[PDB]
Image 1: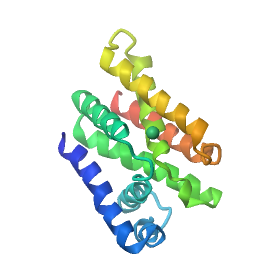
Image 2: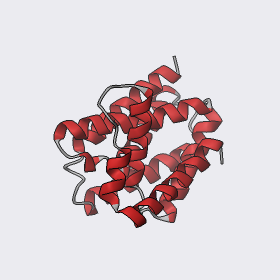
Image 3: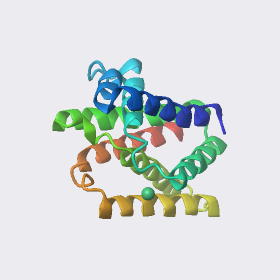
Image 4: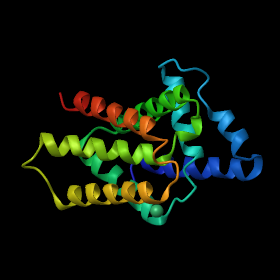
Length: 178
Ligand code: NA
């Protein structure tokens, strides 16, 4: 695991322990961005605010998929670009959810959808560089989002935050490959 990959799953568990003690409403309020200004502090806060909502329906298969994505990303890009991708997509989702009037729409699916969008841009740019590893990541992310569309009551309500995260992912991809 890259240093950023371990921090990710560990921070989820650290926050999950806070929720067990203090309740999710209090913990979400603790980690919510202080404003909508696009600065490093608020982007990092949006990332932690997203993590508050991660343990709910967080399977070992979902964890392994995240690990596989992190490994692939780190093989192709500097580590700092992964942090920026996660923070920028979490912030975009949060800002849009807040505008819609429900910050609880900052759901894990927003991050999975952003990772899928990033991979789809990579596939478009490097059509002669596809590998079984990439093809499997794309397939598994599509299947995860297909299962959420079928079984998560909030999928439709989260359309706008998901779209904002996907657009942020596309913008980061264009930055990382120019
Ligand atoms: Na699942």
